[PDB]
Length: 302
Length: 302
Ligand SMILES: [Cl-]
Image 1: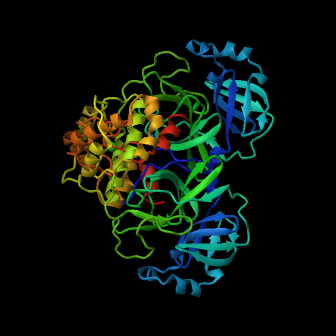
Image 2 (image 1 turned 90 degrees about the vertical axis):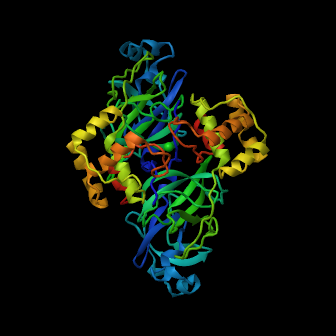
Image 3 (image 1 turned 180 degrees about the horizontal axis):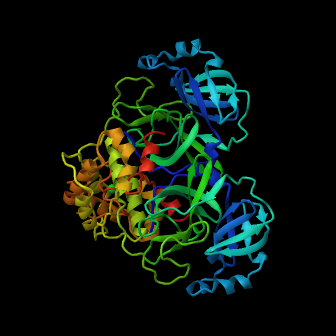
């Protein structure tokens, strides 16, 4: 037995993190080849953030209004340009630590690692999920902005998230590395509703498989259910509906444990209806939804 | 609001991890200057592990029985030697990625990051605590051995743990980087009792401060207590006794929140006696003890 929330090793991302300063605002930037990527709101004053015209604000700014440090190395900004909500600062020097990378837009319920940074220096790494309502439940203090989320696939760093905003309701929102927000959010200090979150049903089932593999079996019961029966119970408890694609994705875990996916759904159903009766599963007293089936396979097979 | 279990960035440790093979056994090694450190049990056969004489087993082994890979780079073992339970393999080449480092022996209830590795390749990073019974509740699959725990202080990687054993009771045990086990454990496949674990009282109080700072206040009550009153309740619920040193260490968190340490103990007391009544604190339904006061300060101040 043994199963923890695991982040990807952060070394490949650490050598890409820089410090971006505009006026009283300093936050984080991502230096890949000759381009530093950061939130375009670095160019805003506390005042501007209320109702920014980023076209007109970006026109008033000059190269030299951007102060980009990497440890010591002051990097010289030789151009500035806007892609949706991300600022691209062109610099004189191509990062010699630039890993093999792609930019990807992930789906809701997928996980990624965040390298949490303050003034362009890495502080910590943690594992996150994209909530179904396209928010992130994270740790971002006041200069955490422009910190990035990522996955490592074979030899390639897949950058999927850049941190932009804390919402007045104390949740986080941000963009892909092309500057398109996840969810309905805008880079403006206004009231913005996240709307109803749900629990990532396929993740909870992945985690129940993780629990069986690590010896935790009390919640296995003598029932199956159909997808319809289950989804009627899911909808009552604000669980995401389960699709046949979800059942297909859980197949290997099914095969490893000899427990059919609908058998495990019948377990989940009872846990939703009667709670845990004061017991725990993998040392937790609530149902965990921030492990994907892929995360559980990786950790339960190396 | 926002508070997650955070590991240290792992980049400085990633460039030190190698693959060590002896016979059918391959595990992980830590390459600092011209020395690879791994568990001495790499030299054991499944059979030997039952009752190993490591002096006599190490004498039969030659340099060339040790196969040490770093990515590609086959490293040539030019000597082999034993310090308590750690094997030091001398190699021809000094790691050009050797960070500034120290070896430290941590106390029970302190935290550290583990870079979890399989065949000398980093898989993941997670935050751990040294349990009061000197075990680690972690994720170590069958080639996770020789993976290391560490802290980063200013510019210095402080290596504090090397993974050696899973105990038949499914918990983990290992050594400092001088090869002295934490706790009563030996590197022999026998039955070994961990003995009674307790909850790290000072950590739970640190985490209740974290909860107040991030807006979670339902459990604040109108009571104080003395250290004696509290420790009588602690001992019943297998909590570590709280000392004046513990109260001293929580001072800054006390000052930040305007809540006296004994006031928070009076909160903890009620939570131990009546449970949570089906509520949560920082999204958890049980009391968390794997954040130190130092971890909470770092995360609630950058
Ligand atoms: Cl919990």
